[PDB]
Amino acid sequence: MSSGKKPVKVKTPAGKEAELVPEKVWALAPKGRKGVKIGLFKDPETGKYFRHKLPDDYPI
Protein backbone atom coordinates (compact mmCIF):
# COMPACT_ATOMS: atom_id res chain seq x y z
CA MET A 1 0.00 0.00 0.00
CA SER A 2 1.02 3.61 -0.37
CA SER A 3 3.14 4.94 2.45
CA GLY A 4 1.52 7.81 4.26
CA LYS A 5 -2.22 7.73 4.54
CA LYS A 6 -4.91 5.09 4.11
CA PRO A 7 -8.46 5.74 2.76
CA VAL A 8 -11.73 4.01 3.67
CA LYS A 9 -15.07 3.76 1.93
CA VAL A 10 -17.16 6.19 3.93
CA LYS A 11 -20.59 7.77 3.69
CA THR A 12 -20.58 11.51 3.71
CA PRO A 13 -22.99 13.68 5.80
CA ALA A 14 -24.27 15.07 2.50
CA GLY A 15 -25.42 11.63 1.37
CA LYS A 16 -22.53 10.60 -0.79
CA GLU A 17 -20.36 7.56 -0.65
CA ALA A 18 -16.74 7.87 -1.47
CA GLU A 19 -13.47 6.58 -0.31
CA LEU A 20 -12.03 9.32 1.74
CA VAL A 21 -8.84 9.44 3.63
CA PRO A 22 -9.00 10.26 7.35
CA GLU A 23 -6.91 13.25 8.28
CA LYS A 24 -6.76 12.34 11.86
CA VAL A 25 -7.33 8.93 13.36
CA TRP A 26 -7.91 7.98 16.95
CA ALA A 27 -8.97 4.88 18.78
CA LEU A 28 -11.17 4.02 21.68
CA ALA A 29 -10.15 0.61 22.88
CA PRO A 30 -12.04 -0.59 25.97
CA LYS A 31 -10.75 -3.77 27.57
CA GLY A 32 -12.99 -6.71 26.73
CA ARG A 33 -14.43 -4.77 23.84
CA LYS A 34 -13.18 -4.04 20.38
CA GLY A 35 -10.88 -1.20 19.51
CA VAL A 36 -13.12 1.20 17.67
CA LYS A 37 -11.53 3.88 15.68
CA ILE A 38 -12.66 7.24 14.50
CA GLY A 39 -11.24 9.32 11.75
CA LEU A 40 -11.79 12.88 10.78
CA PHE A 41 -12.66 13.35 7.13
CA LYS A 42 -13.57 16.17 4.84
CA ASP A 43 -16.94 16.10 3.13
CA PRO A 44 -16.43 16.95 -0.56
CA GLU A 45 -19.96 18.17 -0.94
CA THR A 46 -20.30 20.78 1.76
CA GLY A 47 -16.64 21.12 2.58
CA LYS A 48 -16.92 20.46 6.30
CA TYR A 49 -14.88 18.08 8.36
CA PHE A 50 -16.73 15.21 9.85
CA ARG A 51 -15.59 12.53 12.18
CA HIS A 52 -16.69 9.02 11.43
CA LYS A 53 -15.97 5.70 13.12
CA LEU A 54 -13.67 3.50 11.21
CA PRO A 55 -13.73 -0.32 11.31
CA ASP A 56 -12.07 -1.83 14.36
CA ASP A 57 -9.75 -3.85 12.12
CA TYR A 58 -8.76 -0.73 10.18
CA PRO A 59 -4.96 -0.28 10.24
CA ILE A 60 -4.05 2.86 12.12
Image (cartoon, helix red, strand yellow):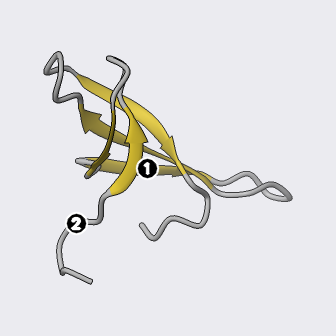
Q: Quadrant of the N terminus?
A: bottom left
Q: Position of residue 32 (x, y in %)?
A: 86, 58
Outermost residue to the right: 32
Nearer the observer, 53 or 14 = 14
Relative to 24, is 15 on the left or the right? right
Residue beneath the point at 41% across and 42% down: 10
The amino acid type, in three-letter code, at marker 2 is Lys
The answer to whether the residues at label 2 and label 1 have Cβ atoms under 8 Å apart is no
Label 1 sits on a secondary structure element that is strand
- Pointer 2 local density, CA inside 10 Å: few below 14, some 14–19, many at least 20: few
Name the residue tied to disc 2: 5
Is residue 59 or residue 32 the one in the foreground?
Answer: 59
Q: Secondary structure at mark 2?
A: loop
* Left or right of residue 20: residue 57: right
Residue sitting nearer the eye, 29 or 51: 51
Three-letter residue code for mark 1 = Trp
Q: What residue is rendered at 35% in x and 28% in y?
A: 12
How far apart, in angstroms, are the residues tagged by discs 2 and 1? Answer: 14 Å
Q: Residue at x 46, y 70 (%)?
A: 59
Work out whether 14 lies above or below 1. above
Tell me if residue 25 comes above or below residue 2 in the rendering: above
**Of the residues under marks 2 and 1, which one precedes in the sequence?**
2
Residue 41 tag number: none
Percent x, y of residue 26? 43, 50
**Quarter of the image where the C terminus is located:** bottom left
Image height check: is 4 above or below 29?
below
Q: Residue at x 30, y 59 (%)?
A: 7
Q: Residue 53: percent from the left, percent from the top? A: 51, 41
Discs 2/1, front: 2
Q: Tell me the residue that label 1 is attached to.
A: 26
Q: Is residue 34 above or below residue 14?
A: below
